Amino acid sequence: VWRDADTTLFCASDAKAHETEVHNVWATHACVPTDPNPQEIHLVNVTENFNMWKNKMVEQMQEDVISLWDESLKPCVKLTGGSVIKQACPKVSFDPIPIHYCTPAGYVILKCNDKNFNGTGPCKNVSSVQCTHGIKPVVSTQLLLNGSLAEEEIIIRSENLTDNAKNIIVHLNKSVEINCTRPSGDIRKAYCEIDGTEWNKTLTQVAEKLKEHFNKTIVYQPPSGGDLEITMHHFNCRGEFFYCNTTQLFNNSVGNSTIKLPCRIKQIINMWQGVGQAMYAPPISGAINCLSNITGILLTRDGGGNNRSNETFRPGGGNIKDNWRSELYKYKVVEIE
Amino acid sequence: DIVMTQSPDSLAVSLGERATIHCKSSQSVLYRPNNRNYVAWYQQKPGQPPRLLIHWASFRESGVPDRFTGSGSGTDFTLTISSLQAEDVAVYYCQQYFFLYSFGGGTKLEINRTVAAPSVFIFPPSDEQLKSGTASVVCLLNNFYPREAKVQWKVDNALQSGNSQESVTEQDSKDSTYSLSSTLTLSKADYEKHKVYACEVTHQGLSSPVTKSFNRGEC
Amino acid sequence: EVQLVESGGGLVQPGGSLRLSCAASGFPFNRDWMTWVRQAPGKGLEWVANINMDGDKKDYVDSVKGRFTISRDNAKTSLYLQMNSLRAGDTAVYYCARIRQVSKYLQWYPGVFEMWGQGTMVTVSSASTKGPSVFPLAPSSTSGGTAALGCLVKDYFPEPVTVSWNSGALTSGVHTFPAVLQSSGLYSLSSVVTVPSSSLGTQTYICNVNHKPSNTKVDKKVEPK
Ligand SMILES: *[C@@H]1O[C@H](CO)[C@@H](O[C@@H]2O[C@H](CO)[C@@H](O[C@H]3O[C@H](CO[C@H]4O[C@H](CO[C@H]5O[C@H](CO)[C@@H](O)[C@H](O)[C@@H]5O[C@H]5O[C@H](CO)[C@@H](O)[C@H](O)[C@@H]5O)[C@@H](O)[C@H](O[C@H]5O[C@H](CO)[C@@H](O)[C@H](O)[C@@H]5O[C@H]5O[C@H](CO)[C@@H](O)[C@H](O)[C@@H]5O)[C@@H]4O)[C@@H](O)[C@H](O[C@H]4O[C@H](CO)[C@@H](O)[C@H](O)[C@@H]4O[C@H]4O[C@H](CO)[C@@H](O)[C@H](O)[C@@H]4O)[C@@H]3O)[C@H](O)[C@H]2NC(C)=O)[C@H](O)[C@H]1NC(C)=O
Ligand SMILES: *[C@@H]1O[C@H](CO)[C@@H](O[C@@H]2O[C@H](CO)[C@@H](O[C@H]3O[C@H](CO[C@H]4O[C@H](CO[C@H]5O[C@H](CO)[C@@H](O)[C@H](O)[C@@H]5O)[C@@H](O)[C@H](O[C@H]5O[C@H](CO)[C@@H](O)[C@H](O)[C@@H]5O)[C@@H]4O)[C@@H](O)[C@H](O[C@H]4O[C@H](CO)[C@@H](O)[C@H](O)[C@@H]4O[C@H]4O[C@H](CO)[C@@H](O)[C@H](O)[C@@H]4O[C@H]4O[C@H](CO)[C@@H](O)[C@H](O)[C@@H]4O)[C@@H]3O)[C@H](O)[C@H]2NC(C)=O)[C@H](O)[C@H]1NC(C)=O
Ligand SMILES: *[C@@H]1O[C@H](CO)[C@@H](O[C@@H]2O[C@H](CO)[C@@H](O[C@H]3O[C@H](CO[C@H]4O[C@H](CO)[C@@H](O)[C@H](O)[C@@H]4O)[C@@H](O)[C@H](O[C@H]4O[C@H](CO)[C@@H](O)[C@H](O)[C@@H]4O[C@H]4O[C@H](CO)[C@@H](O)[C@H](O)[C@@H]4O)[C@@H]3O)[C@H](O)[C@H]2NC(C)=O)[C@H](O)[C@H]1NC(C)=O
Ligand SMILES: *[C@@H]1O[C@H](CO)[C@@H](O[C@@H]2O[C@H](CO)[C@@H](O)[C@H](O)[C@H]2NC(C)=O)[C@H](O)[C@H]1NC(C)=O
Ligand SMILES: *[C@@H]1O[C@H](CO)[C@@H](O)[C@H](O)[C@H]1NC(C)=O
Ligand SMILES: *[C@@H]1O[C@H](CO)[C@@H](O)[C@H](O)[C@H]1NC(C)=O
Ligand SMILES: *[C@@H]1O[C@H](CO)[C@@H](O)[C@H](O)[C@H]1NC(C)=O
Ligand SMILES: *[C@@H]1O[C@H](CO)[C@@H](O)[C@H](O)[C@H]1NC(C)=O
Ligand SMILES: *[C@@H]1O[C@H](CO)[C@@H](O)[C@H](O)[C@H]1NC(C)=O
Ligand SMILES: *[C@@H]1O[C@H](CO)[C@@H](O)[C@H](O)[C@H]1NC(C)=O
Ligand SMILES: *[C@@H]1O[C@H](CO)[C@@H](O)[C@H](O)[C@H]1NC(C)=O
């Protein structure tokens, strides 16, 4: 007999104590080594419910990643409209590492192993687990990078589908590699390469998975104009902040060719951690490169009294908690009394 | 395990013409997330270690000429030599590195040139070898084409048989000809007896069988 | 320059054991995957084994598991292959090769073999080691202004012998015929070189035979008869 619970969880990672990289430095003074033998108990004849959208584990990771960037990627100037804090700006070795989340004494984690678990609802396959899988705190918009993959079909995640402005998390079952690079002109000029045939295939597969829910024609369109972090593919690569134009990825005219998305490394950004803006030093020297798995897509549907046949979807993230949701969705905490 | 099958097993291409070599993998070596094919082509010249020509199916290594071009996807791959050069005579191997490693069977690329008659030499046994119980008469056929040649031995007009061995060089990388050596081994007794030694060469480039000879004892 | 030099090799009795070594130089050896690949005489290339920078990742071809061991010494920049229970099917030329990493499954995996050594010959047979007897092949041999002389390397085992001409000066018209196995069970080849038929006296010609399986370095001088 056990019901729900909410507790201050602890973290675990294979973080090296000698590494200069800040994800290791943070997990060295905040986490412990991973558990060698992860005992998992496939408790069958069990049926309990989960909710990724009301999961406090997502709130805890949001804190830990914010505090990580706070002591690591220290912005030179920070704005909240009022507070104008001005700090030193040294460069940093940056590369996310897996982060396991586990429970204290008395509490424990339940994992829903139904391979089509859509985020909310009951599961039969539920096992008694001890820690979560190694999640890399990759912060990004539009495209989920370097995460886990849906084992069977594409999982369309949301809180209320048939309600309009609620962010969608498309969980792909096959990765599509994206290869972003700043060469060695302009130091801020950069670009990502991505195979068009494979991106067309998966976006076609996502369009079919969207037709199973809504009996209409699915169309992709670039966002009409929010902030730059929402309209473009915004991600952090080795400290430097990339803004990559994805018009060529979400215009329904994705072609055969290897697509080169124009990118830029901007110094003044809007902060994902909270309200306000930050400023960082100009980018480092040499060649800056990040090769990433695209494991998920963040979408927002075009609403309105859609007696129209076409249903338009546009890329947009914004809420970084949803990034930790697409990895922590299969984890609910309980308490044995 | 992945098995690679090349085709053809061997071929002969004239100078300046196209040479096409195919490679088939047992299963797909195409990794879809990056649209890359984990196939390489290697060139092995006669008497040399293999040399990497092309990686990832279609990418040339530095220094390799433009005439080499790899292509294909999935399980069907092709190496094409646009305008064949003498230095291209070799055995070509394809290789997959998608799961572990495995090589194709190999494709021997011969070069077809104009018929060239052999120049025939003949070497007497050495005095160092004579006082040991064995004589070796070496008959040399230098730079000829095609490879088919017939060497016939004569010791005092007697046609020798079953006591000689031949050895053919690989095709030269510059003139595309072959060289052949026929060694006639006789004991000390039978060599000191007879006086005239000759090897008779019949080849396509010669309108008459050629006899080159030496007499036992000349300065 | 990049230089991979294989060592060991020679005659091994059937069921015997042997250890090959590869002396590497000219590249960060302690940061590269390395591999062994063999080629049976007249047949094709067959990958044998490979190993990562730190020695904890090794892989073997099936016909080899259980009796070969690949290893390395990063302090010595050397690759090793311990062979046990050798059989006739193991008779081959064993190549040392440097592996170049390649992206596969978003990780770093061993890929193409970008640089190769010259190879060492391993012969598994029921015979014994025999050094060769070298004999001159004097001129006279001379055709269209071109003289041909050589050295006859006879009755040796096992392969190979390496013949050069004037240390390494002569390379034009040099033809080292393949070894042939005579009825007695020993090998024999002949090496010839074509030169202008007027250096007979104004340019000394000597051959340098070497039979590493039996420390022999006969150097014979060739001159007209
Ligand atoms: C989503 O997730 C993605 C997956 O993780 C993620 O992508 C990853 O991003 C990482 C961060 O950017 C990135 O880390 C590494 O990035 C580079 C790339 O390293 C590769 O290339 C190296 C060079 O390869 C050539 O040379 C080798 C040695 O000769 C040779 O073996 C190769 O085959 C190749 O040779 C060819 O090319 C030569 C010329 O280039 C040519 O002469 C030759 O003939 C050949 O043709 C190579 O060394 C690397 O291999 C090692 O490192 C990887 C790292 O994972 C290991 O897997 C691999 O097994 C090797 O590890 C061994 O070797 C290293 C050192 O040799 C040992 O330390 C290990 O213990 C082990 O023994 C790799 O193939 C690297 O240069 C980076 O290295 C930096 O940073 C690390 C930080 O940890 C330090 O440890 C390093 O010491 C180094 O930092 C020092 O040096 C620099 C330069 O002086 C300084 O500026 C620093 O301040 C510091 O002093 C780094 O490891 C990953 O590669 C990348 N994975 C990919 C692309 O798959 C992605 O970012 C993520 N996305 C998001 C959005 O988050
Ligand atoms: C980004 O996203 C992408 C997805 O889009 C992610 O890609 C995924 O990456 C993971 C790894 O990171 C990868 O996992 C598997 O990779 C290998 C592929 O396995 C396939 O191929 C195997 C070989 O098949 C051939 O041989 C067999 C036997 O001869 C034959 O039967 C076949 O017909 C073929 O000819 C198959 O064995 C395998 O299959 C089994 O497994 C699948 C499920 O994977 C199952 O459905 C089948 O029914 C079978 O049960 C499959 O088809 C695979 O090799 C990996 O296994 C190795 O690693 C794991 C984990 O470390 C080990 O536990 C395991 O023991 C393996 O280790 C052996 O193999 C490696 C290979 O190099 C050797 O180096 C190693 O030394 C071991 O070798 C010994 O054993 C061999 C026998 O297997 C033997 O031959 C050898 O001599 C040695 O004795 C691993 O399972 C996954 O597939 C990728 N997904 C996709 C869709 O591509 C990517 O990770 C993402 N990036 C990030 C950063 O997250
Ligand atoms: C993600 O996307 C980025 C950008 O698109 C991409 O980066 C690219 O990486 C490749 C490496 O795979 C690199 O390719 C060449 O890099 C060098 C450029 O050479 C130029 O100059 C040559 C003459 O000087 C000329 O022939 C070339 O055509 C080119 O114009 C070049 O040195 C490299 O060549 C060496 O390395 C490759 C292995 O990749 C070998 O195949 C070559 O034979 C050669 O090796 C020889 O030389 C080296 C020393 O150079 C020596 O150490 C070695 O032993 C051997 O003797 C490459 O041909 C691109 O330049 C680079 N592009 C950019 C814009 O940065 C990433 O690769 C992408 N990532 C993924 C996973 O796809
Ligand atoms: C990933 O999910 C897609 C579905 O989105 C799978 O593709 C389906 O495969 C079945 C099998 O017959 C077909 O009937 C469907 O029409 C397919 N759908 C689409 C959209 O193509 C796919 O098999 C899954 N796995 C992989 C590796 O892609
Ligand atoms: C997820 O499952 C719940 C359970 O009934 C359902 O209400 C919701 O519509 C489902 N969402 C999707 C995208 O299938
Ligand atoms: C979701 O949105 C629809 C559309 O307005 C609404 O009827 C419904 O009450 C909302 N909530 C749930 C749980 O479906
Ligand atoms: C992205 O590029 C397209 C085509 O050049 C352009 O129409 C669009 O305005 C760009 N997006 C932004 C945010 O500038
Ligand atoms: C790519 O998708 C578009 C529709 O968005 C389609 O017209 C085109 O044919 C697709 N490309 C291929 C190669 O099928
Ligand atoms: C759509 O994007 C593709 C790249 O995939 C590009 O080639 C094409 O020109 C774009 N078309 C429009 C109308 O933007
Ligand atoms: C895409 O490729 C297919 C075949 O590969 C071809 O039929 C089609 O015309 C191409 N489309 C474009 C826009 O290049
Ligand atoms: C070479 O070409 C000739 C014709 O020029 C032909 O008779 C001969 O068969 C060819 N040789 C080979 C090995 O194909």
Image (tube, rainbow, N blue to C red):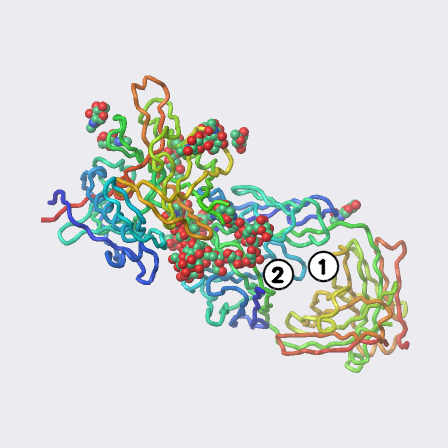
Identified at 48% across, 48% down, the residue is A183
CA distance separating discs 2 and 1: 15 Å
Q: What residue type is labelled 1?
A: Glu
Q: Which of marks 1 and 2 precedes in the sequence?
A: 2
* Quarter of image, res C11: bottom right
* Quarter of image, res B182: bottom right
Pointer 1: what residue? B170
Q: What residue type is labelled 2?
A: Pro
In this rendering, the count of numbered labels is: 2
For label 1, the crowd category at 10 Å Cα-Cα, with few meaning under 14, some 14 to 19 and many 20 or more, is: many
Please report, as a chain letter, where disc 2 is located. Answer: B
Residue B185: % across, % down: 78, 72
Q: Are dots 2 and 1 on a single chain? A: yes
State left or right for residue A94 relative to residue B127. Answer: left
For label 2, the crowd category at 10 Å Cα-Cα, with few meaning under 14, some 14 to 19 and many 20 or more, is: many
Pointer 2: what residue? B49
Depth check, front residue: B21 or C127: B21
Identified at 72% across, 50% down, the residue is B85
